[PDB]
Image (tube, helix red, strand yellow):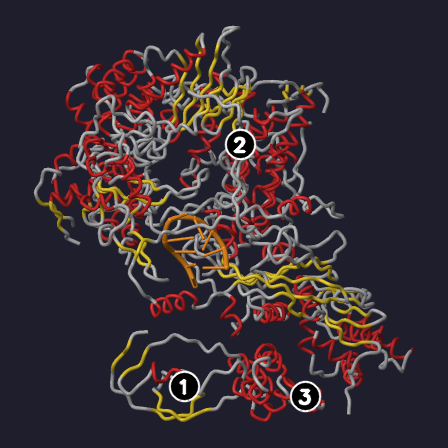
Amino acid sequence: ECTLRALVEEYNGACKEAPKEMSKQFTDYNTFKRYTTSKKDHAPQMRLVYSVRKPWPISMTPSKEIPLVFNGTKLKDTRTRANIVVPDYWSKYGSQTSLEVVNAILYAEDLKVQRFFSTEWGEIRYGRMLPFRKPVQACPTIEEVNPASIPHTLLQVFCPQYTTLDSKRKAHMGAVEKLKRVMEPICKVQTQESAVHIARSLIDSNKKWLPTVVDHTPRTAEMAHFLCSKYHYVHTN
Amino acid sequence: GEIRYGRMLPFRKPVQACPTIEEVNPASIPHTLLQVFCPQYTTLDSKRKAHMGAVEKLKRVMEPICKVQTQESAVHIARSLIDSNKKWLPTVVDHTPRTAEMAHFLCSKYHYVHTNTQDLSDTRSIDNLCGELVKRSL
Amino acid sequence: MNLFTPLSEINPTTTQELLYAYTGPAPVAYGTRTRAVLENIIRPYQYFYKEPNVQRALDIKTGCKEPEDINVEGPSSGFHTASVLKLADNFFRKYRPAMEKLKYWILVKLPKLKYAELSKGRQTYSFIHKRNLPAPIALEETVEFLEQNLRRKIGPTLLSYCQAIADVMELDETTYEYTIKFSREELWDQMRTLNTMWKHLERGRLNRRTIATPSMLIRGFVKIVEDAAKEILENVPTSGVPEKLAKLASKQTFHTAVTGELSGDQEKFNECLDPDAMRLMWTVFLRKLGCPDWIMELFNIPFMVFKSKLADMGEGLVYTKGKLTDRKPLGEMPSEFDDLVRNVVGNSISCRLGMFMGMYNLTSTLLALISIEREELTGSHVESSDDFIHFFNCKTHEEMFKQAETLRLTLKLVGINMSPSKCILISPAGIGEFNSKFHHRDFVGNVATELPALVPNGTNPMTDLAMGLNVIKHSVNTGQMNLCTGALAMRIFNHAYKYAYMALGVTRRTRFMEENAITPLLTNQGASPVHSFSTMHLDEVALRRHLGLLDEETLRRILNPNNPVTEDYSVPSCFKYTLSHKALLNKEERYQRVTSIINKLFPEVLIQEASAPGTVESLKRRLELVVE
Amino acid sequence: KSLLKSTILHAERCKEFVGNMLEEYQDPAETTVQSLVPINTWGKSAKRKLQEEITSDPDWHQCPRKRAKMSYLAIIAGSIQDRDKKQTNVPRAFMLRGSQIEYDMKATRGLVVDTTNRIIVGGETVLREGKGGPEGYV
Amino acid sequence: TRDPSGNCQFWGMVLLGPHHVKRDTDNAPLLIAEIMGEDTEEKYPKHSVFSLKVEEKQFLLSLKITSFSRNKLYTFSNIRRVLIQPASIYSQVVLSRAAENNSL
Amino acid sequence: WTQMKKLPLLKEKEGPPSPWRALLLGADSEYIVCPPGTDQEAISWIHSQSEIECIRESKSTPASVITCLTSSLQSFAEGNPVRSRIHEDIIAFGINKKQEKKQSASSSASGEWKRAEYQVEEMSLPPWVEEEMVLLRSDQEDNWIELEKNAIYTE
RNA sequence: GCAAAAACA
C-alpha cells in the first residue's frame, strides 16, 4: 500500500551503493549469509558483565513512543542506542497488542505446559536400574512428519504460491492445514523472520539420545530428564 | 626515546635539581626535620607547622639510614629529600623534564630525547579544590 | 588421594569423577609455538628406523617400510605397503552394508553438497591478505580470485569449486583484484602452507600442543574426504561414534572363559602416521567398490597435497644472551633442530612424512579400524582417534596374550604405536575406560571433561536462561549429573544469571524499577525463579502464565510484535535485545544490504537453501511477479 | 559526615543551624541539607519536635548527644517537603537520598553512633568522653 | 560480606593498577590486602604482614604484589561450581541407600 | 606382556617446601566484624579506627605499599572507588617494570646467544597442606551458602 | 611479580 516501490528502492540503492557485490548469484546467499568481519570470540559470556554495565547497552530501533527522559532518567541516545532499563519500562508502560497474536507468538511453547501438568506421574520407585541411552524423538508433534519432508511442509504454510509441483507431492498432507490456524496471527512479514522457528517446532521430529529404561514414547521422552535415572524411576500416567 | 636533532632556542629558567619524596614549603622544613629526628625536643607549635605526611615518609626512609649515618649526615640527607633546590639551566619549551637530573641526557642545543612522563602530583586536585572555592565564593 | 578411594557402600569407579580438575583455570599456552612445531615435525623422522638416524630419514618421500624394521620396543613411524593393502582388503570384505551406503553417498549425494558450507569452518590464513581471516571471508575472497583468474563462473556444487582449483593451478600467472600478482610456484607453496597455532583450553596433559589448519584451496578436498570417512564410520560397529561402550558392556560370555578388557591410548598418534597409508586405504576401497577414475583423483588429491605440507614454524626459537631474550628463526644459530635446517622454506618448513592435529581425525580412525580387521583377532574393538578400548573373548590366557600382542603389532604395521604406559589390560572383563566414560561391571559412567558453564551465555536474558537450562538438562540426561547436582547447578546458574543482569542487591536497574513502581515479574528482573528440576525444559513466559505469576496484561505489553527491540525455545519479547588498517569493514556493510533485501522478499530461504539457477538483476523477476 | 562534625563538635554552630532550620532562615548548609534528605513530609513534625525540645531544655547545647538529636531534627526540618501530601510524624530513622546509609535519631546505628564511651560519626570517633582535645590547647 | 545480623565482615581489599590490558590472557597488576590469622615465613615468603589494631583487638594484615589474568579471575568468580562434585558423591551415596530398600 | 603384583610407587620430589601460591589466602582467612552499613561505611570505619605497623617485611612486597593501601581505603571512604596515582604506586603494580628490565638487560648484556633452556625448580610437600585440610573443616556459626531455592511442583 | 618450556608487567 504505497510502500511497494520502497522495496524496489532497496534494489536501486544496492546497485548504486554496492556495485559488483550484489551482482553475484543468488545461490551465493548461503556463503555471505553469515558474512561478518567481527572475530568469533572464544568466550562471549566473559563480556556480558561489561555489556550490561556498559552505558547504552541496547541498540534499539528508532521510535517516538518511548520517552527520551522518564522521571529524570535518560533512556535513549537519540541505529540509536537504548538504556539498560528500557525493557522493564516496556513491561509496564509499553504498547498494547491484539490478544490473538499473543497466543500465536507464545504458541508451540504453551503446549509443553499443560501436557506436563496434566500428567499424573506416580510414586517414586528407587532401585538398581540401568538406563541405556537410545535415540528417540525429543518432543511430541501434532502430526507424524517424515524426515527430509519437513521443509516442504513449511513451504506450503508460508509461500504456497512460490513452490514447485515436485515439492507438492513430497509434502505431509493432513498437517499443512493445521499450521495455518496457529500461524495466521504471525503470518505477516512483521514477525515472519522468526515465525519459521515456531512453525517448525510443531512438526519437528528430531531424534536425540535419552535415558530409556523402557521404550520411551514422545509423550514420555520430552521430560525424561527426571522420570528415570540410575537410582529412581517414575511411572508416567 | 628517539633522538630528534634540531636547532633550538634555549629558555633559561630555574628547575629543581633532584626529585623530592614530598614537597614542603621552606618555612616548614626545620619543623618537619625536628619531628622526624628529635620529637622529644619540640613544642606543639612546631608539630603544627610540620608536614606530617613528609614526617611519616622521612621516618620510614631514615629508619635504616640513621643506623649507618651520623646525626648531621642523616639530618641533611632528609633535608635534601624534602628540599627543592632549584637551579637555573637552559631548557627547551614544552619539553621541561620537571627536574634537571637528566638534562645532560635528554636535552641539548642540538637534540632532545622524547620521554613520556606524567605529573603524578596532587597539584591538579588542589586546582580543582581552589576552583570550587573560587566559583562558590564569587 | 586416600580420601578418593572408598572401601564401603561405593566403589572407586564412581568417585573417579573427583579426579577431575574442574572449576579451575584451564592451562593457557604462552609464547612461541616454534619449538613445539619443530618437535612435532621432527618426531616422525626419529622413529622411522629402530636406530635413530634423523638425517637419513629426511629424504624418504613415501613412508613405506620393510618388516623386521618396525620398532617393536618403541614408537615407529611409517607403514608396510603389503600390510596396508591386505588390511584394507579385509576391512572391505567385512562391513558390506557400510560399503554399499558409502557407494550410495559417493554416487548420489557427493555431487550435491553446496560449496558454501566451507564458511562454517575454522580460522583460515588468507594467501592474499597475508593474515588470518574468518572462514566466510576467506571463501568469498577465494571464489573472487577464482572468478578473476579463471573466467568461468563457479557452480553451486563444490565439485565445481574443486574443478576450478584444479584448473587454476595449471596457470603460470595469476592476479587478484589491490591488483597483486601470484606466480604458480608461489600459489603452490601457499596451498602447501599449513597455518599452525596453539591449542587453547586443552585440559588433561602437562605439555601444550599445536594444531594446524589447511588453506581454503585444499579445504574442499579435505571436507569431501572427511565427509566420506564420517559416512563410512557411522555404519561400522568398531567406530567410536554412534552407545558402543554400553552395547559391549551388555554382553554375556561363557561361564568359565578368559574375557580380557584392554583400555589404552595412542602415543605420538599424529607423529607416526603417513598420508600414503591413507592413500592406499582409500584407493583400495574405491577400486574394490568400482568407482570411476576421476573419483580416484578426487579422493587422492588431499593426501597428495598434504604429503608436501609447509607448516609454519611459529615466530622463532627463543635465544638468551644474558637477561635479554630474542626470537630467532631456525638456522640462524645452532640448536637441537639443526637437521631440519635444510628443509626451511622462508618462514615455513617442509616435512614429507608426518601428521598434524585437526586435519584428519576420521581417516586416521579408519586406518586404525582396517588394522583391527584380521583373522586371529577374534575380539571387540572400539576406536576413536587416539583412544580405544578392546574386549578379548578367548579360551586361554596365552591366547589372550597372543591376541593382544598381534593387536599391538598390527597397529604398528600402519604406525599407530599405542602407548605402553597408557595401556591397561584386565584379565577378567568388567573394568575399563574409553573416551571420558568409565566402565564397571554392567554400569557405564559418563564423566564430563568440562562442567557446565552455569553462567548466562551473554546474548539476552531469555536466550541465556533457555541455553543454560538446556545445557543443564543435557548434562543430567547423559548421566553426568543427577537430582541433587542438577538442582544445585540450576540454583548456581540462577544466582549468576540474576547477578549478570542487575537483578541482585542495589543497582541502576533495581533502583529504576523501584522508583517507578515496576514490579519484577521475571527471573532476570529479580522475581523468584519459576523453573524447577522437572520444569527446566519449559519456557519462562509460558510457564508463568499457567501458574498465574504473569498477568495477561503484562503478556500483552511484552509480547507486542510492534516492539522497539527484537535450541533456542524462547518466544520473542521486549527482553530479546542485542547488545551493542582493516579495509574490510565497508564490504561487510554492503553485504548486509544484500542480506537485508533477502529474508524480506523470500520466505523460501528461511526454509531451504538458495537453490535458484542463475539469478545474478534476475531478482526483478520475483518483484514483477509480486506486482502481477 | 562533614555537616555532622561541624554541628556536634561546636555548640555555637549547632545553635545557628537549629535556629536557621527552625525559622526557615538562610543557612550556609541549605543545599547540603536539601540534598541529604529525600523528598518527604516530615518537616512540620520535625519543627514541632524542635519547639518542644528547645522549650523543655534551654540548656541543650552542651551535651553532644542532645546536639546530635537536635541536628537530626533540624536536618529533617530543613528538607525539601512535598506539597501534594499530608504531613506525617517524624520517623526514628531515615535513609539518605540516593544511598543506603541510615541516619538514626537515637544514634544507635548507621551514620551516627553515640556509645557511652564515645561518639562515632561516619566511622570516625569525633568525641571521646575523657581523652580528647576538641576545644584545643593554649 | 554480611553475617545474618547486619554486621559487615571485612575479609580484605584488592587494588587494581592501571592494567592497560589488550589480550584476554594478559596479566593485570593487583595489590591484595587480606586479614591473616597466623603468619608463617616459609608458607608466605612473598607476603608482607602488618599489625592491625581495631577497637583494641588484634588482627594481622597481609599485603602481596600479584598480577592475575582476566581469564583466571573470571574462572575464580565462578568458584561456587566446586560444590558440584562433593554434592555428586553425597547424592550418589544417599540414592544408593534409597535404591537398596525403596526408602529415601 | 607382563603382569604386576606391585602397585606403582610414586617418587616424592625433594627440596625446599613449596610456598603458598594462590590468589587469596585460603585457610588463613579471617574477617573484621564491622557495624552494619554499606561498603563505604565499613571502609570508613576501618580506615578511621585502625593503625598499621609492619611486623614482617618481604623483599618481594616492600612495606611502602601500605601507603597505597591506606590511600585506597581513604579514597573509597570518601566515595571515590578509583583514585589518582601516587609515588608509592610505582613499585606496587610494576609500572614501567618491563622497560626497566629491558634497558637494564641491554646495558648489562654480555656473552653470546644460547638456547632458552628453561627450568622448573622441584619442591617437596609442604607441612601446611595437612594443616590447610584440617583447618578448612572447622565448624562455623553461619551458613555461608545462600543459594535461592527453585520452585517445586512434583515430588 | 604472575606464570611455566615464554607471554604480561
Residue at the (63%, 65%) spot, across then down: F56
CB atoms at circles 3 and 1 under 8 Å apart?
A: no
Real-space CA distance between mark 3 and mark 1, rounded to the nearest whole angstrom: 32 Å
Mark 3 is surrounded, within 10 Å at the Cα level, by few (under 14), some (14 to 19) or many (20 or more) other residues, namely few
The residue labelled by disc 1 is B100
In the picture, measured across the screen, residue A232 lies left or right of residue C613, that is right
Q: Amino acid at mark 1?
A: Ala
| Element type where label 2 sits in the image | helix
10 Å crowding of disc 2: few (<14), some (14-19), many (20+) = many
Read off the chain for label 1.
B
Q: CA distance from mark 1 to mark 2?
A: 67 Å
**Residue mark closest to the camera, 1 vs 2:** 1
Quadrant in which the N terminus of chain E appears = bottom right
Marks 3 & 1 on one chain: yes
Q: CA distance from mark 2 to mark 3?
A: 69 Å
Left or right, residue E20 beside residue B62: left
Secondary structure, mark 1, is helix
Which of the 4 image quarters holds residue F77? bottom right
The kind of residue on which mark 2 rests is: Ser
Badge 3 or badge 1: first in the primary sequence: 3
Q: Nearer the viewer, residue C545 or C384?
A: C384
Residue C63 percent across, percent down from the top left? 21, 29
Judge whether C438 appears above or below C335 on screen.
above
The amino acid type of the residue labelled 3 equals Arg
* Picture residue at 39% right of the left edge, 50% below the top: C30
Q: Is residue D55 above or below residue A25?
A: below
Q: Which of label 3 and label 1 is nearer to you?
A: 1
Give the number of the disc on residue C475. Answer: 2
Q: Where is residue C124 shown, x and y percent of the image?
A: 28, 43
